[PDB]
Length: 55
Length: 55
Image (cartoon, rainbow over all chains, first blue to last red; front, side):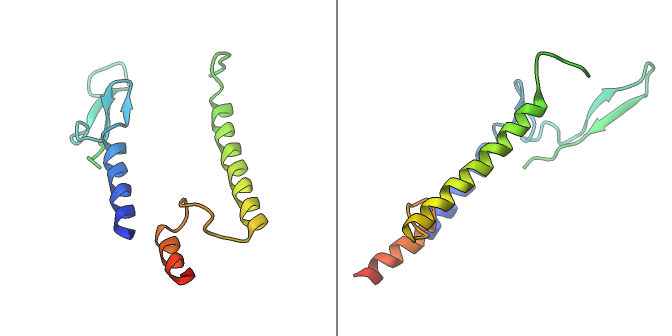
């Protein structure tokens, strides 16, 4: 009976990982494993990198 | 950052009030009966053990 409870809790850790999205882009499934780039200046090279490992 | 279409401060505030109200409700029913395991929300293994002890 205790395992039947642990088993379902692990299913949601999977479910949150595969659901969390920004409109339509999944953020916790490794597409941000190699940090993506945002440009915050007005010239080339002024970038910020955000890395989210798969969980 | 002065908007009149979305109030995210309200959205976060609403969630906290709901959590505090639900905790108050569950405490009253435990006090009104005198049992920690009212439903299967609580210890899944506890109710199974208690049934055999009750027998």
